Image (tube, coloured by chain):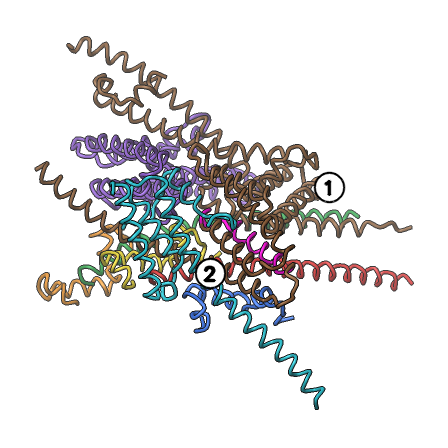
Chain colours: A brown, B purple, C cyan, D green, E red, F yellow, G blue, H orange
Amino acid sequence: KKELINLHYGNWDAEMKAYSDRTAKYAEEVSQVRRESVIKERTFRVNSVVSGLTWDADPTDAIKKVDAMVSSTVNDQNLPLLDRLQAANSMYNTAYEKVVNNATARAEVERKMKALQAYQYEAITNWNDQTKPRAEREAFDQQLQAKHGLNVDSSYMAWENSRKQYIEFQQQSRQLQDLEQNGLIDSARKVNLSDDFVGSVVQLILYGEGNTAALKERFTDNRNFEANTAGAGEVRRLLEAVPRMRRETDSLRSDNAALQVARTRLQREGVTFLMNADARTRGLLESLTPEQQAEYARQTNQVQQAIEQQIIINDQRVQNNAAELAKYGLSEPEDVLRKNAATRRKLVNDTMYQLGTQAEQVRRTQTSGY
Amino acid sequence: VVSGLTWDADPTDAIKKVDAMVSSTVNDQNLPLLDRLQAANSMYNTAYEKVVNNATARAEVERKMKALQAYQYEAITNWNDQTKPRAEREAFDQQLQAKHGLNVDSSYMAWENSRKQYIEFQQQSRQLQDLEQNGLIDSARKVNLSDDFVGSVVQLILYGEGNTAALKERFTDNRNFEANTAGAGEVRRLLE
Amino acid sequence: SKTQQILEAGNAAIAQQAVSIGQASQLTVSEQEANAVRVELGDLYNEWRSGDKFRSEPGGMTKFRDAGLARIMSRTNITEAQKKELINLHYGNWDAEMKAYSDRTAKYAEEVSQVRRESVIKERTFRVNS
Amino acid sequence: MGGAAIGGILGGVQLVAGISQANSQANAQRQSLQAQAQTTVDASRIRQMEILQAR
Amino acid sequence: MGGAAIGGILGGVQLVAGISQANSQANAQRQSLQAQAQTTVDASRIRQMEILQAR
Amino acid sequence: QTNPFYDIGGVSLQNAIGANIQADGANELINFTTGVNTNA
Amino acid sequence: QTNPFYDIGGVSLQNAIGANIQADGANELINFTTGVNTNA
Amino acid sequence: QTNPFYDIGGVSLQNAIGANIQADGANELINFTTGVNTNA
């Protein structure tokens, strides 16, 4: 029976292997079509730009446009490093071939290709290191791109957006302080509003959509003292602590489940459960005639009490973590937080805009009768 | 998801999505143990086959298969035991799943929903107490509404069409000055 | 030929190094297998060019490159230098196709610019003449 | 009815129920944030009206 | 659906997002400038009305 | 509910695809499989 | 999405031109490659 | 009231299924036999 069922299950596994191969072909075709469309669009724009020059046209604008297009291609986050490097190679080679006769433009294109050479040398080494996390490797890759000046044009827009968001956050904090000073908002409400500010900012930085690394670097720069009391330190602490404590909470839940399973097995089977317990339960615990088996039950009572106490401590710590997470508003599941970031920030901004409008009305009506 | 990786792509996101899908499959109550185990095995096998050339991904997938194998070894003994009731067997199976880190996302979502429900319960009880002394509701309507509210909570916990076991665990078992109020004690007694 | 998947660090580094940036770069078992895979790559390129696959298929250039890389990387019994040479040949074919596409796009842009300039010049000349 | 259509629609309704449950959580938080903002604005407006009367 | 169809449409989604993401903030800046100009005009006309009533 | 999915495997795959389309037009499916938000 | 673009190269170029048209009717494309603003 | 139900047995089963449909569109029947709520 065992060998027949094993044969049948292996046959099923082989057929599922074939099905997975077909699905792999489908998904590969889809991704390949997407990447080819993007590359062809970028290359067509570059080519039609570089081909518009006449017999005596100045190529400075064409070279600048090619550089901006290469900036867009290299900084594109949906493409792999190989495709981006190869597309940049094609664009730069076409630009060199078309404008080969102009000495100054040829020298500029050669300098750009040497910059691309050095960037390729460093990015190949940085990208293929398996001892480095994906997020930090991506951050270092963007840092290298900014170092060689490839993505300055593309990164400037996001940098300006992040600066505007930071200025808006500081203005909101100062506005809330002035709102307390005028008397429109009580002290209790300000705690909730500031917690909302910090939670919305952290949600945008962590679970938001798009390359929000610019705002993360903006808030991480503790050297800047501009409104450090506004809550920048709180935002940095939350950014450092939220993923770590979520992982800790998940591990504590797993440990609590292990302890509950161990206690249930100990109650149902007795001391015999300790004979063939798996390694993890043995580590957690570390951290004959019926008479001897009755002494074993007496010891089992104390073991169960200790297990229950450890469960209580772990549950209390998990409760504390979840409570002070929900204090800010980041206790929702990852998908829910991801879908509910931009709207939350927009609601915060609209609420503060209404508050500022009312405060402005009150202040404007403050006029002397003399 | 697994096959969308490029020649030089990093499979961290793909492995996380595989983890989420296996969590959804194993936690699914509408499938038997054999179907869930077999589907999870096929998913892990495909993921391992498509990332064999990456050492870190291979090690991660191998460790997750070891965890799933331990879960299968325990759940074979758990599920086929005929001396236990269905509710106890399902509770022990959920504890086994949470022990090996399989149903992480679903368990976290259920716990968060139960926490929100309990906070709403406390806030509604406090609102009832405020209403009684505010003069809006007299004593008789107040006690009738309190009885109706407690009965509705108990009915939701018992006969609700969902995974309400988390709220039952929250009510019956408590850590510090939670579930120790008169209303929560009455809810525990009614549940029993 | 298996589908594209994740490579080792060394193989991926070799594949990305073969992208020659700048105008400064252009039987035993291993030799026999390298010759066979080179012949296979040449036949694949000939089939793609003659069959009009670069235009009819939606993912032409990317699919050609991915197929070439799949044929090259599926052979684990090939020395690193031979793999570099094969990938260089494949990238040269890809660059030739890209150059042909560039010539076609350049012709299109030249035609558009010439038409516009001719229209303006003919307007002005007709006005002066009349 | 039939033999396969019933199973197909049962599976489909299960999947739709799960997806709509996730979307329902998202929309519930949407409305919760809406209500919180509206309550804050209303309280501030009441405070402003009281200040104007005192003035 | 299809193999090259859905891939084409989802590549087009990325392309159209990239193209229109430049115009989006330009339109937003236009809207903000118009809003601040209208606020300036409204405040100035309120002050003018006060001056006329006093005179 | 389209022939390529039949070619990939089974008819129940068509059932799953139709279920996703009826749910959100395969928005979550496209987002989770490819990483592209069809309706941002 | 026109035969000249197919003749220039691929079907992917047709997809790119269709994306440009769906975005702004190739306004940005014509401005970038040629320097003429169709919609001033 | 469908040919498969006649194939299972009798015309009386067809009458029973018609009664189920006229009652709630076989909602209670589907829920009780299968455990899936068609109309949650």
Answer with left or right where residue C72 lies relative to residue A350: left
Say the numbered circle drawn on residue A316.
Answer: none
Near-viewer residue (A111 or A23): A111
F3 in relation to B11, above or below: below
Question: Which residue is at a point 42% across and 33% down the rendered structure image?
Answer: B184
Furthest residue in direction bottom, as rendered? C130
Give above or below for E37 relative to A254. below
User: Which residue type does callout 1 highlight?
Assistant: Asp
Q: Quadrant of residue A249?
A: top left
**Residue drawn at x 66%, y 58% as measured from the top left:** E29
Query: Mark 1 Cα within 10 Å, few/some/many (few <14, many 20+)?
Result: some
Tell me which amino acid carries mark 2. Answer: Lys
Q: Position of residue F33 (x, y in %)?
A: 38, 51
Instruction: Looking at this view, name the residue that lies furthest to the front.
Output: C27
- For the residue pair B127 and C113, the one nearer the viewer reads as C113
Q: Secondary structure at mark 2?
A: helix
Pointer 2: what residue? C99
Q: Nearer the viewer, residue A141 or A66?
A: A66
Q: Which residues are magenta?
A: A61-82
Place of residue A197 in the rendered image (x, y in percent of width and height, measured from the top left): 60, 41
What whole-number distance in Å separates the C-alpha atoms at marks 1 and 2?
64 Å
Q: Residue at x 29, y 15 (%)?
A: A301
Mark seen at residue A178: 1
Q: Position of residue B176 (x, y in %)?
A: 45, 25
